[PDB]
Length: 578
Ligand SMILES: CN1C(=O)CN=C(c2ccccc2)c2cc(Cl)ccc21
Image 1 (tube, rainbow, N blue to C red):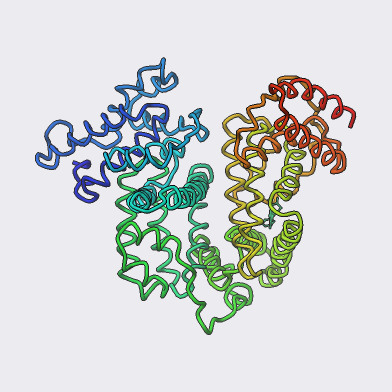
Image 2: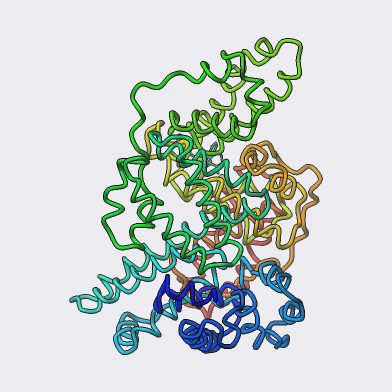
């Protein structure tokens, strides 16, 4: 029995939660109740298997068990139409079907939260249904959320209420911690989405290179053979979570935290504080540990990778290992580069060897390979310098706008919401990274950017409207950022014709928060640009300035929110003029 296996290892608690997550991630539109029911039923069954390891179907794989349970509600096409088809299939096929139908952008109603008085009450009364609810809501809106990490967030969520509800000014103590968590959770989700994307679209060889480079930076002292071990495991971990096998992913992850902690001295010196805490925190901790100091005396790379004469020989023997080595060697001594830059130099090296080794004089051909690295390295360094300089002037909001304009001219087809979303993030890069010293800027900047571009990629893949977006997203995981930066303005885009419905002006905007105010104000700017790709900053600003006067006046006007109707049509007139 497998269900039993996972049960003993995780225990009632975490086993129950994980399965709730898994179900919510498969049937995102299904209600809380039903899920809870299925989870419980499923849990009961497990309990019997622990006792009798052959009872009913205790000999089954989680896929069959989990698959049949959901199918007791999925067959309801009226509710989950395209799902029924999935249940009429067999294993393992019946699952891929499920994995292929996850929505990255569910049509789920915003999730507003009641006053601090109702939450604490609901929390105190029933502490189990309050947290179960939490997981459900997150997991259904983030079908790729790193499950194990979700249990981590959960523990912190509970600690929030458990504390603030016995305070003096609940709202005061709560509100903060809850915002800080809604953010940290969004980032974590993105980070993990990229990981699943890599594995899913580019293969494990690709997820691997990424880990090798990433870990090697974190753990300079570790030895290539050690890292490889870590990389091999890590992959399986994520390979599982992304493929839907949460329980085993949850297990395996622990085993990896156990090990890394046993062999501390062989890996990093900054792991101490991580291994001394509870399991969940231990894991979260290790995953976010600062790089270790760089080993004192380190030979040069040129020695064994360009100057040696057995290069082409070693390359032909086990190119995989030789390149894996090159990457590990370049990374460890360069924590100032981004994972992608590294994988980039690596790919350059490989390509070189490939052509050189088949030449009349190898060592002569691949002799000046570090010359080629020079450009690839300075590029990001320069772009990062520019962009922070700008950001440092414009501030976050105006920086987002600049970026919003630019990307819209690049891929006008892309739906306004996505472009507004994506460009808003693309700007956080500035506030998040720019405040670091050169030595730490690039990894912060370029890898974060890799996440934000993955979003645009996935969101787009749902309904592909621009081939230029498609090319850049599918051509090379490592080269996405450069590919997008190459794009100028689409010269074949034919502007849209205005419409009353293109944008509505209900007065309901005067009630929204300050943020949702900028957001409509930005959703406009996008909209404008799609109509007049050919305007420059002068007319846009001017018009945008105006759009402001409109909301202030008409919102502060005593008339029954109709100036919105009249003045709404008034601006359209002014606008078209520019
Ligand atoms: C989103 N974005 C761009 O499109 C311009 N290119 C970059 C960039 C260029 C090279 C590496 C990483 C990032 C960049 C840099 C900052 Cl500091 C802020 C936004 C931004």
